[PDB]
Structure formats: C-alpha cells, structure tokens
Amino acid sequence: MNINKQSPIPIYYQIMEQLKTQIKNGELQPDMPLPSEREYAEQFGISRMTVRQALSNLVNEGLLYRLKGRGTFVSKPKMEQALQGLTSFTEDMKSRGMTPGSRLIDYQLIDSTEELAAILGCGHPSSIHKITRVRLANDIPMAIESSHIPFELAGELNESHFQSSIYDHIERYNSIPISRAKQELEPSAATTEEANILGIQKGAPVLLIKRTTYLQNGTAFEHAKSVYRGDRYTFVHYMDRLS
Amino acid sequence: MNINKQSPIPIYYQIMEQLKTQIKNGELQPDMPLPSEREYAEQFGISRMTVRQALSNLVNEGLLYRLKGRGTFVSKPKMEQALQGLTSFTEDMKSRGMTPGSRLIDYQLIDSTEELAAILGCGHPSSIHKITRVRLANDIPMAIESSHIPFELAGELNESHFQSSIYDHIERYNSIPISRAKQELEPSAATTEEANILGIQKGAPVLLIKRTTYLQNGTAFEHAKSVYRGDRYTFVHYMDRL
Image 1 (spheres, each protein chain N blue to C red):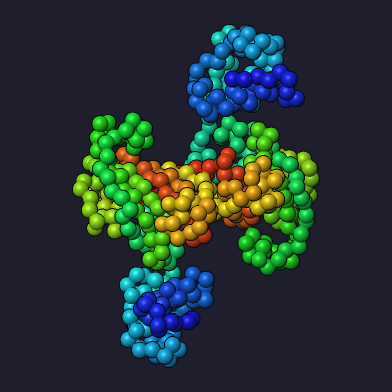
Image 2: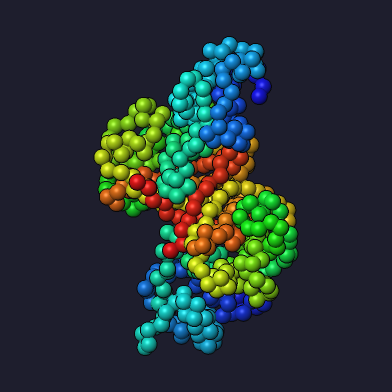
C-alpha cells in the first residue's frame, strides 16, 4: 500500500481507494480485522485522524464495520439481487464494492417515433425523456448510458435525478415495483468519442448492453443503450433450467 | 433469392440457407404458408424434387412443419428456455433458427489441478476431460469452446459425443437433470489463432463466456470457457427483480 503525500488527491482518499482494491484483491478477507488506526498512522507517517477519516468513510458506506472496543472489519457483500435478480447501475456498483455516480452528457425531451413507441409500447405521438450520462465507479468512468423514458412515467426531471438512481425515482414516482428486464449483450470496439470519455484507447474492448425494463404493471418504463468499459466490467448472472 | 448453379454448394443447400435468412429477418412470418414446390421450381428454373429436398430437410429440423399435403409453414420456435432459462449451445442455436454442429480441435484426459478442483468442486487427484471444439452454426464457425468435465460424470467419450450435445449425454449418463449455471461475460478482441479458426479478422470483437453448470443434485459437471464471434452472436436473457 502506497501513499503519495505530494499528490493533489487527499491522503484519506488515497487510503480508501487502496483498501477498496485490497478487499477485491482478497488481501483483506471478509469478517477479518483491519490493522489499527495507529498502525496505519505509523506505517505511512501520517496523522491518525486522516486514517480515521478514511476508515470512518468506508464504514459509513457499508464497506467496513466496527465493533465497539474491538476494531474495524470487512463487511460481507449483498449478492442475491446481483447474481440472481436485476440491479440498477447504482446497486450493481455497490454489489462490487464500488461507489456509483453519474454526470450528465445530454438531456432532451423528444417526440415519440413509431420505432420507440413499439419498443416501449407507449403512446404515439407522445413525449420521451432522452438521458445521456457517464456512469462512474470510484470517480472513474465506467459506462456511457443513453436512456429513453416515457414522460408520464417519470414526470419532470432535473439534475437531482440525473446524479442519482433513475430506478429509485421510477419506483417512487409511480409507487409500483420494477419487476423485470430484457437485456442483450454484444461485444464491440470503442469509437473515438466513447473511448475519450471512457478513459481507454480508441478501438478498445467494450460491452454493448441494451435493456428494456418493466414495471410490475407490465408497462415498459425504459429502453437503454450502454457502452461499458471492457477492462473494468464483466457481466455475471445465474440461469436456471426450466422444467 | 438468388441461385448459383455453377457453385460446388448444392442447389437445395443454397435454397435451405436463403429460406433460413428470410425467416431470420421476417420476410417469412411464423405460421404463414410458404410457396409450393412448383412455384419455387419455376422461380429458380430447377427440378421440383430439389425444392422438395430443401423443404423436407427444413421440416425435419423443426424449422418448418406440415399439416396435410406437401405444403409447408414457418415454425414458431420455443423461446422460453432460451430467454428465461438455460440452454446448451445446441438448443441456443435452434432458438435462433440455426443448425448447430461441432468439430473437435483437441481432446485430452488431464489430471486434476487445485484451481479446477475448487471450481468443479470435484476430487483431487482425479481425471478431467478437456474438450476443445469449434461450435458451428449453419456450417460456419460460431464459437471456440474449451470445457472441463470430471471423468466420472461423463465416462468414456468419443467423436459421437463431441459431434453432438454434451449436455444431453451428461443427463442420459447420470439420469439427473441439468439444473443451473453461473455465467460471466466479458468483451474482447480475437487473438490470431482464434480469428483464423473463427473466420474473422485478428482483433475483431468477441465475447468471452465462462460457464459453470450444475446438476439438480448440486454437483458441478462442467466448467467452460468460450470465445464467440461478435458479428454473429448477441447474448439475450430476461432478468427478474427479486
């Protein structure tokens, strides 16, 4: 583990990021104690309060837990929804021990076409949200997502929606659960503009994910197309044989 | 549809494949009648028996059905298992209206390794089948598959097994149904060897698929790694929110 004191990136943030890597490395195993706050302080020659800030942040994110008078430990993850269910990008990143975020690239409220109407099974003519975001994990681009949503199913949208979970909004606005999705996966090569935004070379491996998601209603509320970085993302799921 | 009579590819084969294309894009709709032998015969300027040969082979593959007379209808394929369950390559290709095939690249009976023991949950030391095939759809390379299978769960394997469905053999051999799989998918670029065998350019998009498959009783019988042509293959599946 390596701290660079002269870097613009705050010491505490350097520590969080590396500890997060050590957890996915398996250098820090679940339910196993972490070095003490003073040990870390001594091992890097830093303030104990900076260590506290890092550790405390990871506890508050649910990545670590603390037992009063007995230290800090790695938390067991929550995997039912990730492997056996359907996750939003936000839940997906958390299942992987990553911190999700989003930055808006483009927002348009567009007129329905027969093609989009067919896919969403919405009204034509009508209004459809078109939301283009960079999805981040640990402040680093992970995907570019273009998302179409019937206006009636989401109402008026703004920056506060774009920077959090759209799935959470949908369920609260409609007071109906999300129930299922059709998804298609295709491999591809990053275009110049996808590559530049994503932080990878032109032509680098990329996963194209097309998803239509449904309310318990049977009503489609979203059709989305995403490009995920190949170096950082693999898709994982269980399948059951029907009989 | 066009027909090249001077081609080494048999006419009835050229017909089969262009009818398959018509279906795959909905120029022929499910459960809608096709033209008769005479109409096709006249269309291409060929024997009626050649058209019949193309249609009858398609009936046998379940791509078409009959009801009465030689007259033929587009089949409406079962998609439930493909989209919501778990299919072998064989069933997967059929759900797409493609004809699956297999050719052996390599076979070895290998000794158990620590990593492989932990994956399949099998014994160590033990013997493991290592089977590398080119998986074909309509006589054209689709995937390269490398699968590890504990000897005891398959017994002795030969060409008759490799050129057919492993999944079916393992169910017949064991009298226990296949239950579930864990799959991981990652995009990549074809190596030189992979690209050559697949019929694509070096560095062309491929999909890496890693699958561990279990029997109804919980035993893992297969750990497979595959490379799929990005130009022919899309992965499709429904997911339910818990």
